[PDB]
Amino acid sequence: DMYIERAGDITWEKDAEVTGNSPRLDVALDESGDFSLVE
Amino acid sequence: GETTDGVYRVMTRRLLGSTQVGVGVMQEGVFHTMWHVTKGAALRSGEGRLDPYWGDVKQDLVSYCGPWKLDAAWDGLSEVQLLAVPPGERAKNIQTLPGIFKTKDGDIGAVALDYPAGTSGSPILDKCGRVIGLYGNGVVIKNGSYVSAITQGKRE
Ligand SMILES: CC(C)Nc1nc2ccc(C(=O)Nc3cnn(C)c3)cc2[nH]1
Image (cartoon, rainbow over the protein chains, first blue to last red):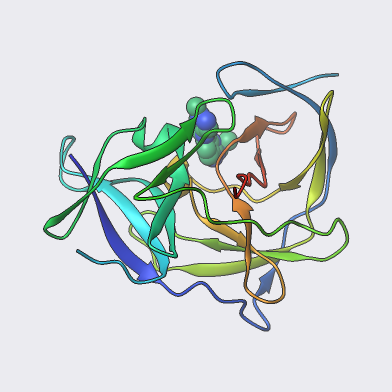
């Protein structure tokens, strides 16, 4: 049995940790909702 | 039970101890999460029951108590925030500029942040705090890191 617990408010926080890159990737989505790399 | 707007953890007592399988968003009385988290199964909120209302395995999304309410979109230009809710750790906002997932049916925004599978369902936000999508359905790239799509549903 699955259950839910509150974890916080949904807000934009100024001066948050800024990380992560922005890659342009060619992908395919299958009938089961799975993404795969197309190269 | 708890119907307050906000981000929630999705847990189970079926495995060892209490295990976090995913995250979801409560908005306008509707609970929104990714399909692979709940597999469409019913949820418990305190002493109340949340029954599924809509779902699609291809979109990897599911809504409880009502129809999908999240309708904001990434504008293709601005940086966004992943309000990550990791297992056993506090809610943490992480800002990044999304990349792209090019598909035969159109481009989709994508966040290059890597978090455990238990983080799936955590919302991605725009400057006004509106939910533009959910994190957790993506791909494993060359260097072994995970890159997730910004997954958004349709509001009728
Ligand atoms: C690369 C590794 C170090 N990290 C990593 N973060 C993940 C987040 C989600 C999933 C995941 O399995 N999603 C999914 C979406 N749909 N389905 C069926 C399954 C995997 C992950 N791996």
